[PDB]
Length: 151
Length: 21
Length: 121
Length: 103
Ligand SMILES: *[C@@H]1O[C@H](CO)[C@@H](O)[C@H](O)[C@H]1NC(C)=O
Image (tube, rainbow over all chains, first blue to last red):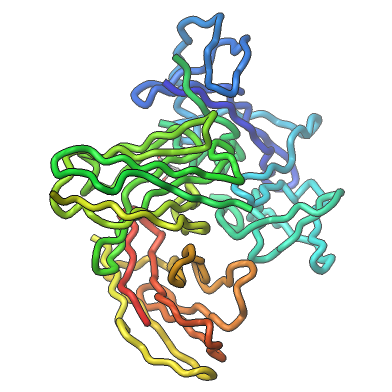
């Protein structure tokens, strides 16, 4: 049995911004998957020994989202509450540049995100050092597609 | 099985994983 | 920076399991990426065996799948290999490499120095 | 059933000229091919990953190319320290297949 904690970034279908409200903690067992009930216990560096834990609920709706089928997954309009907008995964910045003024300090050029593209996975094959309203975020080689197709 | 490939498109990126006894 | 220096017993006897330990130093193994074991046979031919992602998902080479397994550790920044039912032609040099967990873009960036595993009398 | 065949198993060289190494497949793998340089007594260093991208810190001499099934590898202005074994690896599907050596 396995425990996972998840982080997300809002994805923009055009002008408006959307974000998927998947559960914060999802527990897997290889053959079985279920949401972590409460996670009201300390996580030691040695591993996971929850002093107060019990059996977890089952739900085919939300669980199937994590099974790879995003058609019937969580969905939430986040225009009012922007929330997370850029994350660093695999050393490749994941940002929703359609609503954040992301820039590259290698040349000062603005990165253009078009409605046909939802998320831009900026890598070092086009931006060695990136700078979103801050300081040097050194990005390594590519590990992700440059963007995600709308369809 | 969490297909990490499809969750990444909608922005869901795994940030930590472990096991419990 | 990130370095990988593996070690293990290279004098395994035929028809018993082997053991290989890779000590990832300079970067945590549970943060991200995927960790791999690659071996090259005598003859410079390389083969890919299996991966341990940052999460606890794991797949192996279909040829070796029935007798291979990948583990890890958290307090110690290491991930191991237990391959049982060793036959005559499992002798090779086993390498430690780091790659992304997404397919495609599965290329190996940092490699290990390598160690020699022999299967003989 | 992806099998990668690297044709030039041996190639001579001299300091100051260009040499082309090739690799071939049997099923289309797009532009996804990588090139690793193995100096003796050191760790393998990737040079070109998917497409023809220079890895950060790798000299501009090495130049990837190719698409679909047949790729190449071009080295310009061979310095006396550029002699090692160059392998190619396809990273589009599983059963990740490498290639033969080169000198
Ligand atoms: C991910 O989404 C694509 C596009 O809809 C789909 O074809 C694929 O089956 C999904 N992944 C899995 C593991 O089902």
